[PDB]
Length: 52
Length: 62
Image (cartoon, rainbow over all chains, first blue to last red; front, side, top):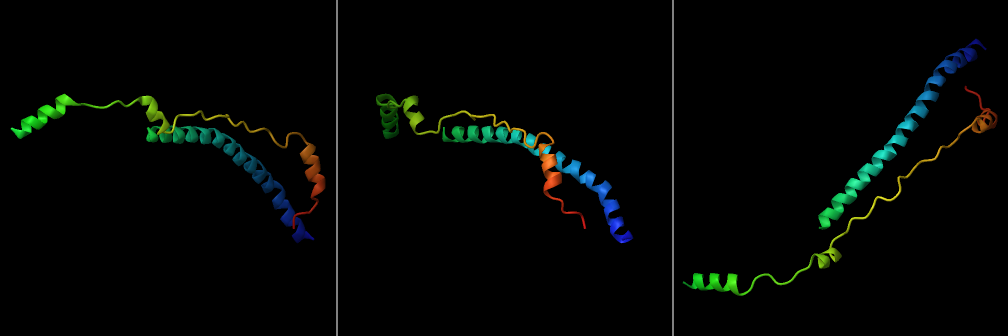
């Protein structure tokens, strides 16, 4: 029973770290969307200009 | 001599023919807007999800 208990003890603290970290990462991808639109506009502009 | 004749004739007697910028437009890809900001909308707001998640998967850590 002590063996079972020891696993759970360590988990309880450390999991909270991952919990935060995971959402933090997701936030970064939101910001990446703003980038994506910047990238997009540049690509489009270069293409129209290339045709000219 | 013949060089002079050619030079004279070419430059003087004909130059560029008509050609419009408007006609050019057809043959090129024109600028168009990058429509949409593309706003993402918040997901999983409130403890509605949390109550659902606590209850839904009760599978304990082993």
